[PDB]
Image 1 (cartoon, each protein chain N blue to C red):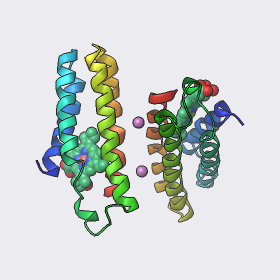
Image 2 (tube, rainbow over the protein chains, first blue to last red):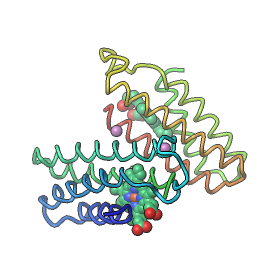
Image 3 (cartoon, each protein chain N blue to C red):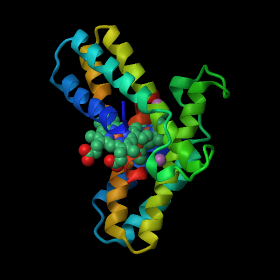
Image 4 (cartoon, chains in turn green, purple):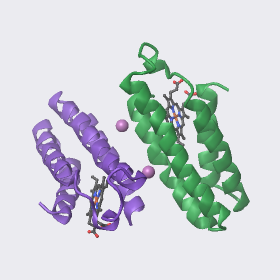
Length: 106
Length: 106
Ligand code: HEC
Ligand code: HEC
Ligand SMILES: [Co+2]
Ligand SMILES: [Co+2]
């Protein structure tokens, strides 16, 4: 899957958590988002075509996925503790990670 | 200033920027936010006095402030371009930084 693929996965599943018909769908969507974020971290965004892999732009790009994954894991723990409403509430705050990285590089 | 007074400065000047409609007003408010953020950036907070200065938790706390200062700086540059509304949208996007650090600390 490519960067555009990974972003569709993240967008589709973030909305699944918002609209989840049952609590089990939240964990399933978080799982898919974690995979998509780790895959996206290995891509080069088009607006950073010309920059070094050691550039601060690419550093901040990759770091954003690390941090996103951290907070997805926080949400998964809540869901794995059966605290599925708390997990759904946490998942809505993930939108800040999307918005922040997009500000820079989308 | 103390932590509570710095946090109030950040809180009020966000609304100053929302209320404003010209570049000088937005720049003035962002400069105040930046000074408030730098004032609070380096102090260990009460809940982590027993944590090492290089502990994962202190590291993430300090990065919260470093990253907030970075985006205030970016918004300030937009205001210095006369891009009032882009500067205002960036300032609204700062709320993600506020809530992220709060949820970690509280
Ligand atoms: C950086 C660390 C990012 C994080 C975190 C998220 N996204 Fe993203 N996204 C990023 C870039 C650089 C781009 C541009 C990709 C390109 O090839 O142009 C995107 C794009 C999207 C898109 C549009 C995809 C497309 O086909 O054009 C969507 C729908 C999207 N992103 C959604 C999304 C969501 C919901 C996120 C949080 C869960 C998220 N992204 C995180 C960089 C980064
Ligand atoms: C850590 C990296 C922080 C960032 C970034 C921001 N804040 Fe904060 N805030 C932080 C602490 C440790 C505290 C004190 C402990 C607590 O949880 O209250 C605060 C407190 C505030 C308050 C007062 C809370 C109240 O009940 O009135 C406000 C109003 C506040 N903070 C505002 C604020 C804003 C607007 C921020 C972004 C621009 C912001 N804070 C960032 C830690 C951190
Ligand atoms: Co965090
Ligand atoms: Co940033």
